Image (cartoon, helix red, strand yellow):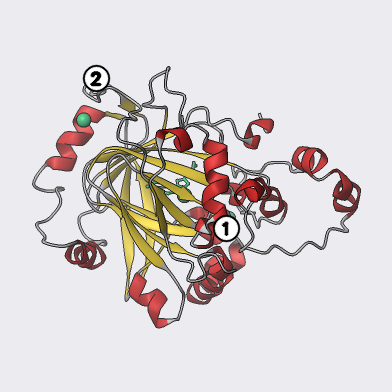
Amino acid sequence: ETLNPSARIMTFYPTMEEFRNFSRYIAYIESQGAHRAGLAKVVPPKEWKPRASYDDIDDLVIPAPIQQLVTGQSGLFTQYNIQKKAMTVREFRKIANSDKYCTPRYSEFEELERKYWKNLTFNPPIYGADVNGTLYEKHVDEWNIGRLRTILDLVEGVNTPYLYFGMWKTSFAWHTEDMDLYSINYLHFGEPKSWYSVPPEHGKRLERLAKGFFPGSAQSCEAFLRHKMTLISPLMLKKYGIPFDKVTQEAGEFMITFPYGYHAGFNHGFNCAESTNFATRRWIEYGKQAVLCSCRKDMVKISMDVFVRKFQPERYKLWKAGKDNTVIDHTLPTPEAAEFL
Ligand SMILES: [Cl-]
Ligand SMILES: [Zn+2]
Ligand SMILES: [Zn+2]
């Protein structure tokens, strides 16, 4: 409670020594209260690079590019997907940089952010989303998104890497991760990516507001935000007193999302990001209490039995019977942070 009381987005600059152990560094940022914002930025040391160059990926195939059609007014929107046929990075880059789809002229970020919210229902862009793969070279052992080696490995497509090829005005809707897990996002190259976040301790406030604005979606599915179709502007959040923060990610930077941390955002122009999900001992309780989508068969569901028997042996008999009345404290850091406190 005393650490990061304002629950604002924190930025970290680790040394090569600190950076070498991923699991230990996540425990350190939690001891500083980074988790309270629900989103944190990590700038890696200058000497670290995951790949020598990105000049040999023109013929990489994007199997399912998606055209994003948006409908709405007065800060409330719904995004619909149209799956297009397979295209290459070369073909996607030519479309992204053409006069029809390129980034507009602007002086400061606040101007581009106004242009995004004013024009998001016009000229639908194409997002090169959910590409199975990695851009990390084999010999890279530090912060390798393809092999983080957290306790989530005990499960084994949530523990595999994904690529995102963006263009101006492509967006990601308000959501938490599958099973309310953590996530890591690295921006390989190109134009920035802007993020919005709601502290996990205020997450139920956002859900109540969203349920009020979309009553039909709430009856059909309790966890309707997991469909990733709902867009809400910062001005609408301010008008209904929902606490939030904003941050811009640049090429070469990492973004970390925390359990039950709601996030949304947009791409400034042509770029490429890589992501995966991970876990700590603290996630276990969030995973047991996660509210899942019930209207879709193909949804992500992990059995918690293995994590409870291995890390909570005393509580397994009670949990499996239905006697676990544990209340989550969102301000508490992970148990692995003890050495820093
Ligand atoms: Cl390139
Ligand atoms: Zn996400
Ligand atoms: Zn659903």
Q: Residues within 10 Å of mark 2 (few under 14, many from 20)?
A: few
48 to 308, vertically: above or below: above
The image's mark for residue 260 is 1
Label 1 secondary element: loop
Look at the numbered disc 2 and say if its residue's Cβ is closer than 8 Å to ligand 1.
Answer: no
136 to 130, vertically: above or below: above
Residue 64 in picture, x, y percent from top left = 37, 35
Task: Answer left or right for 213 relative to 290.
Answer: left
Looking at the figure, which quarter contains the N terminus? bottom right
Q: Earlier in the sequence, mark 2 or mark 1?
A: 2
- Residue at (61% x, 54% y) in the render: 295
Q: Is residue 138 visible?
A: yes
The image's mark for residue 56 is 2
Residue 159 in picture, x, y percent from top left = 56, 33
* Residue situated in front as seen by the camera: 144 or 287: 144
Label 2 secondary element: loop
Residue 289 in picture, x, y percent from top left = 71, 56
